[PDB]
Length: 297
Image 1 (cartoon, one colour):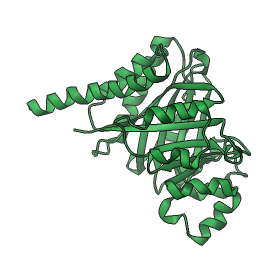
Image 2 (cartoon, helix red, strand yellow):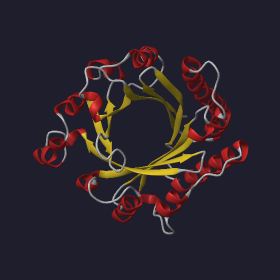
Image 3 (cartoon, one colour):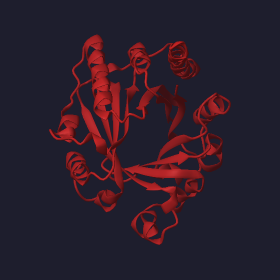
């Protein structure tokens, strides 16, 4: 149908525009191999979302970070996994690197129940230092205790981190271009549960008061369990991206990113990632800021 082809061509350009807006704001030259990711997202014709993010370390700005979230209502998770891995393979072929897939392979095992997947994403964090570049994948699972246990066994180990095992749904994979790979498990708390007394006992009690303040403006909180034995990275799903400066004490580099995105044609919400110790400071020096746009027919 003519409406369909016109819409498809439009969504393709809008995705490229979203990526280009981010890249052109923060990197005067695009970081290699960004075009392969552009090819990947434009090959995904079903409904999706894109994430563009910045990682700030004092005055250092790392901005070639993009993810695609598969959001076609058909629930064809295995197909999307395969599409994502095909993309990873092209990256391997063009750059001339071999990715270490072992953690993902072990996680998937041989009997993975794809109907238990609720989120799948694939993307990049590209650096001029090739070895430090990575491919990324997140898989969120629901009601799948066997795979939660498997992900737990695959990461750093048991205690500590075990105190939040029952809150884990999201599993993240990093695949570095130097053949090093990582897995992380994320414990989450949803907004509707923020004020429950057992949540204070099981979760909030083990974090400083400063960690709790941004929850006033968040719909979801999560934290990585295996990495950073102490000083865990805390992630907040801000309902409105405008609220960032009210809850997080930004440095100049982060303010630059915030300022850029205030009036872009993007989704209202954002994610904010920062180490626990940063919120205890008078000024955050290390922060990750995540912005989103949806692409639907």
